[PDB]
Amino acid sequence: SGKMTGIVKWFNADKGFGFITPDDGSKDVFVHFSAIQNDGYKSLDEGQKVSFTIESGAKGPAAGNVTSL
Image (cartoon, rainbow, N blue to C red; front, side, top):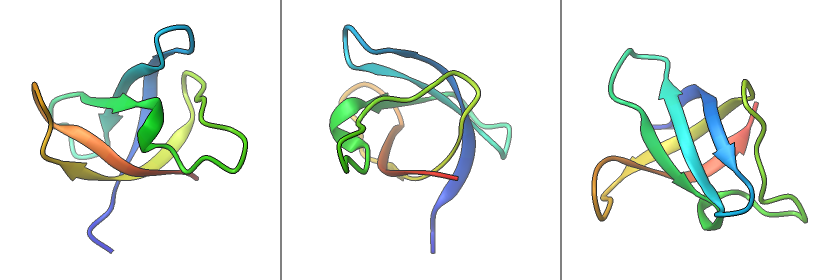
């Protein structure tokens, strides 16, 4: 797919958001808990490999369809 891969830079489980460092060296991408493929998870750990799509974000590039790798 047109899915980018990256690593979770940080994730604040109390606020439900964080950033992803894309593997292409481009700007960090905002991730909202609601963008995560749920299955009774919806949380992310610093350093986790993820796959996502880059989407139209309210303030910058946002991750959509976030999957664990």
